[PDB]
Image (cartoon, coloured by chain):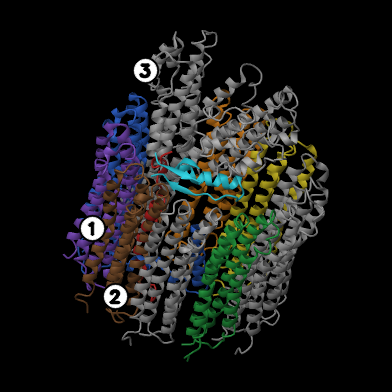
Chain colours: A red, C blue, D purple, F cyan, G brown, I green, L orange, M yellow
């Protein structure tokens, strides 16, 4: 057996849910860096 | 067989992937960063562009360096033959020592051959020194390919 | 804060490895048994999905790099906005590379019998499809970004002078060698891999 | 052969197939809607022809919705790891592809609707660029709908 | 160059398009062959200036109206590029206009000491250096009641850190000191902004373009202090910026430079500024070196320093057109080819 | 008593409050380019 | 084995995250597009009651989270299957991390739109049209979570 | 097995979390919008007790966190079920990490609303209405956690 | 049921009750002290009137001290794991909420004493906002006291 | 044994180390940041030099608070000590250390801002001392918490 | 069991860490003070041997590590107790991470005092008086580790 | 037990590291110095071949890595001792992470040296001497790895 | 058990570290002070062989690392005690991570000293004086590592 706590199925759920959470953190850091061009909305 | 376990092709296909991905990463840095400097002098003296395509060609050779060792690792991988863990560790190491070799050589060619091409529009006598520094920065991947070929022939 | 987590995970890995090694149980951190006992369908499906995912995240990367500068450079010189679309095309072909490799890989994806499930060949064709999906998706990623950068420079040098696009299309050719080389290597890696049996 | 943790991968694939696709569609709607709102304060008659990038970003989210619905009709308590990881792959494919295609449509769309108000010949240019970025979601949808057909065989 | 075109894709390609409208050497020779300001207008109409003097019609056309409208379209192009900017780019565009805000402050508070009317000392102000409380600098005379009333809500407020108001209100001698000290603190802050948040290809070629501004301002302060100033070097060293190529060894010798040779022997030890103070027009040497530093900032592609390198080159283009139109209107043609063209 | 553009009412309030330290009762009533009154 | 003890953990995380991340999305949509209302209704306050539509369409995302949180909460149990916990985790994330995206888009489009609608009154219809495409993202996440939650306890053992 | 020893850990950390993240969101909503009150009531000191609304609506979030941290606490106990601990952890997170978002959206709206409602008196009702839409997020987290905590000890063996 | 590693959670709950409330009180004292020492250079008569944000910061550390003493006098070697978990929760409840209360008191106190010298009527508004900022730590005190009242209630 | 394992003095040595480590970090910040203000406001006003050293004395008291608890945890370490003893010695060490660290941050920031502006207004000297007292009782509280944890380290241990 | 095989690991890490972090602190205190000296006496070089006091007081807190990393080194055996290794690790950290703080404080006070002592001649007494309080930090760490190391082998078995 | 099956992993990554980090340092030393060569030989064309000595000096680092990696490669075996893998890992790190250091040093010295040697002709000898002091670091790493690799397979057994 | 199979790992990464972390501090002391020589001797090239003393004193600490790496290398064996591996790791870290500090200090002091010794020639004897204190920090680590390495195989058994 691989382990009793860190079994064959838990340890490859925590790789899938680490890859997906990595893609999520990257995509949320893309959307967090999204700013509005305010000079093209004002009168000045 | 205790010397040839069934997880050994993991480290051989990892050697294939490290030999291809990092070498084409180095080749892409070397062609993109240098194409920035070649296209930057596109208006100022356009006649020096077709002479300055050498750091793009020498960057593209770094992908051939990874292609050769990726073919030679993938030719030693079959599901019917026995495949030792020694062979898998050796293919991991020979892909890993050519991938970062071509990556560093591509970073060096990209940083040299755009500054050189970008200063070459002022001084037309730079070209021999530019080609010389590109040869010294392109043998960096040839060293890693030599180590990878010797290591492939040793590990099989 | 991310450097704090990078240091904390490193400290926890070193403390766990040295605790497991000092107490005579250091072979319990067993990466080989992890590779032997995880399902080959994880590696196969993950390789297929990351192949077609990372080809597209490089294709779409290059498309906006040489699209936004094409539209910016086309404001004064609008006679580039159709001729220079081959720079979109050269960074778009790295997605059809990953697509036609992902379908060829998914042809090797059948139901294996449970009595021969963690066999030599079934585990081989999980490893091969995993790394041959990685080496195609990452190569098409890097090729799409490089062709996008060398097309963004070409879209502005085209609007500068018309005779420069022919000279800087060659750099896009040498940049688009890379995705085709990844296309070759990912077919050679999963060339001897059989189906799941 | 069919463990107890096997519908985790299918449920998280059904999750990610709409999560990553809606993140990409939200970036493609928001960033290209900033360009619509910035463009149409000085030339407001281009408002309903500049609306194409947010429509294409919506088509991306429809492509992700299709995969999420078609994965959640094949989930069961006692499915194999084969079905679970093939639903995971069908989720990851359309997730990364819709995310990439939505980022590309967002970054191309605001630049296109800004160049279209200065030069009228750039409308056909931005449409022909955005059509290449639209079908990348189709390129992940193909792998998702092919891995769906191999779910229970 | 991998994350540049997210927010700066459209911005660069239009500025790169604005670069192609820079007049070349042949387009300057075709302007020096003109005989009338009307012929110069019609020669500029074939360039990318086309029909910018269309509402003039050959009668009210002077050599200052050309400098007005040719710079006005520069300012409107800068405002169009700034309106499409967001994030660090928009902040970089604001930091460019701060140096014009300083000149408009120092031009607005000299029009009140001389009691010149407020409506005519503001048409001479710079349009890019406009802040909303710029006409309200005509309310007080001393520095403290112009800071604490007007210049706190301005973005020029962190730059009043060393301006010591000794309750002497204002002559013309200390407004230049306040101007040089605000520009000193501004060059410090904008160099730290470029070093901090601007990415790496647009960092090294912008630190040189900004250290050149600091070196030129150091030489001009240390050379204009001979004729119309009698100041101590410990008070003169607060006017010289410390970001440039010239600071740590040569601005010390420019601080205790009591004679012209104290400047010349100080600038003989620096390598790229030696020979400027020997022969020729010094202002032409600085403008030529400015254009040679702006030329090789277009040769690096994915850089936001192309905006600075564009607007300084376009300002030099407006200066060259103004010099040519001044030559062909006053009928002096002995130095018509004194323009500066690196494009 | 006078007229003013509406985008300058707050900056006139702040400049008069920084000139006269306190010492004022400033109102505004919108005139119905948009403008505004002030006392 | 089919119904373990740690099985309500994923169900409780799915009940929590559905309201947590939609409250984050609705909070960004209220926040970013309410700064624009408070900035552009100091000059033209007559259109205060029509700029409120980004805030309302942001607050619909929190109701999308609330519905799925209640429907996951009334299916939790001590002896539920691990399948039920996995489906409730997926239905919680499918509403939460999609309504977070919808709320980001509503906040960005609303702040960019209520600032441009005071200079050009014809941009209001375009703002509403873009915000409908931004709100159907959270609606699609609601559809996915309802189709999961109908599948949650159907043929469980 | 069904009620293990580590079972009150999740309940105690949920009882902690429901006041920790709630007080953090309410502290952002108090500080960020108190900056605006202390900046605009220098010019207009007559509007102190009128612009105090976003600080009070930030405190109502902390009251929502307090009334769940005092209901999880009396449902705690040694040898309680692991299901009860998971439900209490979920009800802790649903109040805390959504009142965090509601406090962000109250603070960064209320500061701009206090900056704006000293110039335009008609913007104050719009400020209150946007703050109601920002405070109903924490109310929704309260509703989800009360409906969840009602099922913590309901027929649990 | 009452293991050996059980007072670890109680010791961490006794530490974290005073650690994070002292961090919050230290942020509040630092921000408010920078405010006072920059607003009382020109107005020294209202120096002792502006020390109220620093007092409101110190009451947060007193709140942490009370919970840490009450958790300290309930520790033991042979205590339950339930008692350790409740003491950890009662430490974190007062600590990470007094940290937030200290952040709010520091920001509000700095912004209020920098503007209360200009407008004398802003003092009764600053006190009113700091009451709402100090009730944020009083809530964590109430949660910590109600937890610690049940740490040893029905314990075997 | 079970109540007193072999790895039990690890937590005691970490609690003896941390109590002086983090208070030395806090006292070092309170000395350096508030000594910059002393060395900057003495080139024009050198007559107030022996009275502006209040924020470095009040910061060096934090290091004495760490030293006392480090000595008292050091003289309670044993090889066959309980695991409860090591746990609450770690607790005492963290209670002194991570609170004296915060007290040192507050003393450094307040003392810098106070000796920077006390050279301008002489009536601010009685104010910055009254703020530094509230900044130093933050470490005094951690001292009290660790002296109450250290009175229970070997009290009813078996 | 009381003296395991892995027991000299903590003693060797303590013997290394006693001198490693004091060398880092002494390096910082020497580096910033040397920059301050070399920038303050290009105009007044008469204060060269006068301003050497921060470099000396930063070099003393490395001798503080050199003492304890010899006294820990001469108590390292193969068959030593784990209690001895724990105390030697605590002593190495107690000198090291306290002399690092002392070196930070000496390095900041040193150049801040030698750049200002070229202007005011009687800031030198104040600089020494602050550096004594900055160097007793490393002295306190030395006292703590010398009291630990006198107990690492007192009543061990 | 003493020559395990996973034992050539350490020797394989030691053979890899002596190319990876050494080529990374040599690439830094060639790139950053070639920037200075191409930036100063614009107006000084005759010094184009005197300035290659930083780039050659950095290429000798990669030759140092090449030699040690080949000499490790010709001692990898299937039935290899774990001691031998540990020694080869140490010898690979000792060349790689020291040639990276020498490459950093040559890359930072050499561009400043070719920028100052175009302005002062007597600074060339000083540049060459500082580059010798910078290359001797990678020479020290090669000396350590050649003395270390010679001890792999001396008294190995089983 | 007392001399396990993984015991030469710590000795190998102590032989490797004593040149890695030493040479990447010597490289900082060479590069950061060599950009201060090449930028100063463009106007005072007669001081070229006098300002190069920071580069020499940065090269001396790499020899300090080389000696300890050779002495740790020649005490490695296949069957050595784990105590010997721990002692050799401690000696390698004691040289490497303190010669790194000495190299940082020499690099920061040396360019500040050579840029100032050309304005005032009486600052050279102060640069040497500060630089001896900056350079003895690696000699202290060499003393600690030699006193460790003399204790490595003294009374080892099994």
> Splitting the image into 4 quarters, where does residue M142 fall?
bottom right
Question: As rendered, which of C192 and M55 lies closer to the eye?
Answer: M55
Q: Secondary structure at mark 2?
A: helix
Q: CA distance from mark 2 to mark 1?
A: 25 Å
Q: Secondary structure at mark 3?
A: loop
Q: Which mark is residue G82?
A: 2
Q: Determine the chain carrying the residue at label 2.
A: G
Counting other residues with Cα less than 10 Å from the Cα at mark 2, is it few (<14), some (14-19), or many (20 or more)? many
Residue B154 in sight from this viewpoint: no
Q: CA distance from mark 2 to mark 3?
A: 76 Å
Does A31 sit left or right of L89 as displayed?
left
Q: Which residue is mark 1?
A: D65
Counting other residues with Cα less than 10 Å from the Cα at mark 3, is it few (<14), some (14-19), or many (20 or more)? few
Q: Nearer the viewer, mark 3 or mark 1?
A: 3
Tell me the residue at 60%/45% (across/down).
F19
Residue G50 in sight from this viewpoint: yes
Does E113 sit left or right of G31 as displayed?
right
Q: Which mark is residue G83?
A: none
Q: Which mark is residue E46?
A: 3
Please check whether the numbered discs 3 and 1 fall on a single chain: no
Q: Determine the chain carrying the residue at label 1.
A: D
- Percent position of residue I55, x then y: 63, 69
Q: Is residue M138 above or below residue I59?
A: above
> Splitting the image into 4 quarters, where does residue E153 fall?
top right
Q: Secondary structure at mark 1?
A: helix
Please check whether the numbered discs 2 and 1 fall on a single chain: no
Q: Determine the chain carrying the residue at label 3.
A: E
Tell me the residue at 19%/76% (across/down).
G155
Does I48 sit left or right of L50 as displayed?
right
- Percent position of residue G104, x then y: 36, 55
Quarter of the figure that contains the N terminus of chain G:
bottom left
């Amino acid at each position: 057996i691989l382990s009793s706590i860190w079994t064959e199925g838990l340890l490859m759920c925590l790789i899938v849910s680490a890859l997906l959470l990595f893609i999520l953190i990257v995509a949320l850091s893309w959307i967090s860096n999204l700013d509005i061009t305010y000079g093209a909305l004002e009168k000045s | 067989n205790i010397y040839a376990p069934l997880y050994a092709p993991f480290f051989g296909f990892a050697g294939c992937a490290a030999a291809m991905v990092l070498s084409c990463l180095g080749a892409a840095i070397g062609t993109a960063k240098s194409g920035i400097g070649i296209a930057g002098i596109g208006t100022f003296k356009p006649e020096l562009i077709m002479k300055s395509l050498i750091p793009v060609v020498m960057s593209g050779i770094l992908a051939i360096y990874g292609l050769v060792v990726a073919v030679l690792i993938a030719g030693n991988l079959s599901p019917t033959e026995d495949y030792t863990l020694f062979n898998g560790f050796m293919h991991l190491s020979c892909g890993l020592c050519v991938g970062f070799a071509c990556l560093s050589s591509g970073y060096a060619i990209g940083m040299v051959g755009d500054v050189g091409v970008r200063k070459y529009m002022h001084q037309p006598r730079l070209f021999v020194g530019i080609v010389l520094i590109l040869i010294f920065s392109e043998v960096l991947g040839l060293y890693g390919m030599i180590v990878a070929l010797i290591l492939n022939t040793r590990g099989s | 804060f991310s450097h704090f987590l990078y240091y904390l995970v490193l400290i926890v890995v070193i403390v766990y490895g040295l605790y497991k090694l000092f107490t005579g149980h250091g072979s319990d951190i067993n990466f080989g048994k992890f590779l032997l006992r995880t399902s080959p369908y994880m590696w196969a499906n993950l390789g297929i999905a990351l192949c077609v995912g990372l080809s597209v995240v490089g294709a779409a990367w290059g498309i906006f790099i040489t699209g936004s500068s094409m539209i910016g450079a086309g404001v004064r010189a609008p006679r580039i906005t159709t001729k220079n679309l081959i720079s979109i095309i050269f960074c778009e072909v790295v997605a059809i590379y990953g697509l036609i490799i992902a379908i060829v890989f998914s042809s090797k994806l059948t139901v294996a019998t449970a009595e021969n499930m963690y066999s030599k060949s079934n585990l081989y064709t999980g490893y091969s499809l995993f790394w041959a999906g990685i080496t195609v998706g990452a190569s098409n990623l890097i090729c799409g970004i490089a062709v996008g950068i060398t097309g963004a420079t070409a879209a502005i040098s085209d609007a500068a002078d018309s005779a420069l696009f022919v000279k800087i299309l060659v750099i896009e050719i040498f940049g688009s060698i890379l995705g085709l080389l990844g296309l070759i290597v990912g077919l050679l890696m999963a060339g001897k891999a059989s189906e799941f049996q | 052969l069919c463990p107890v943790y096997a519908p985790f991968f299918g449920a998280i694939g059904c999750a990610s197939a709409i999560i990553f696709t809606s993140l990409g569609a939200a970036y493609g709607t928001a960033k290209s809607g900033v360009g619509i709102c910035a463009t149409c304060v000085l030339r407001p008659d281009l408002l309903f022809k500049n609306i194409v990038p947010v429509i294409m970003a919506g088509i991306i989210a429809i492509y992700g919705l299709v995969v999420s619905v078609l994965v959640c009709y094949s989930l069961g308590q006692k499915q194999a790891l084969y079905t679970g990881f093939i639903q995971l792959g069908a989720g990851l494919s359309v997730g990364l592809s819709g995310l990439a295609a939505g980022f590309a449509i967002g970054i191309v769309g605001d630049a296109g609707v800004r160049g279209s108000s200065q030069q009228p010949r750039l409308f056909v240019g931005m449409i022909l660029i955005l059509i290449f970025a639209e079908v990348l979601g189709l390129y992940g949808l193909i792998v998702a709908l092919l891995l769906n057909s191999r779910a229970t065989q | 160059g991998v994350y540049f075109n997210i927010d700066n894709g459209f911005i660069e390609g239009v500025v790169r398009g604005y670069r192609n409208g820079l007049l070349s050497n042949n387009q300057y020779i075709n302007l020096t062959q003109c005989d009338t300001l009307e012929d110069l207008k019609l020669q500029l109409s074939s360039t990318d200036y086309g029909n910018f003097l269309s509402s003039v019609s050959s009668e009210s056309l002077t050599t200052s109206l050309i400098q007005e409208y040719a710079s006005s379209k520069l300012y409107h192009e800068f405002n169009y590029i700034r309106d499409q900017s967001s994030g660090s780019t928009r902040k970089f565009m604001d930091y460019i206009t701060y140096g014009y805000m300083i000149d408009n402050v120092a031009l607005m508070i000299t029009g009140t000491i001389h009691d010149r009317d407020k409506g005519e000392i503001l048409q001479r102000c710079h349009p890019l250096g406009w802040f909303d409380t710029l006409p309200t600098l005509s309310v007080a005379t001393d520095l403290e009641s112009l800071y604490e009333t007007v210049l706190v809500d301005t973005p020029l407020a962190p730059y009043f850190k060393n301006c010591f108001d000794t309750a002497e209100e204002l002559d013309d001698m200390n407004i230049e000191i306040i101007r040089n000290k605000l520009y000193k603190a501004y060059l410090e802050d904008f160099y730290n902004f470029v070093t901090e948040e601007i990415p790496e290809p647009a960092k090294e070629c912008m630190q040189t373009l900004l250290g050149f501004e600091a070196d030129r301002r150091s030489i001009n302060i240390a050379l204009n202090s001979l004729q119309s100033s009698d100041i101590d070097p410990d008070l003169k060293s607060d006017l010289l910026p410390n970001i440039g190529k010239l600071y740590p060894l040569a601005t010390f010798h420019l601080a205790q430079a009591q004679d012209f040779e104290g400047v010349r022997a100080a600038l003989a030890n620096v390598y790229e500024y030696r020979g400027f103070l020997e022969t020729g027009n010094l202002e032409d040497h600085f403008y030529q070196l400015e254009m040679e530093l702006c030329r090789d900032a277009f040769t690096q592609q994915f850089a936001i320093s192309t905006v600075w390198a564009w607007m300084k080159s376009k300002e030099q283009e407006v200066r060259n057109i103004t010099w040519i139109a001044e030559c062909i209107a006053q009928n002096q043609r002995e130095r018509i080819n004194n323009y500066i063209s690196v494009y | 008593t006078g007229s003013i553009r509406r985008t300058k009412v707050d900056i006139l309030n702040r400049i008069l409050w920084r000139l006269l330290r306190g010492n004022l009762i400033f109102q505004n009533f919108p005139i119905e380019v948009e403008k505004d009154c002030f006392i």
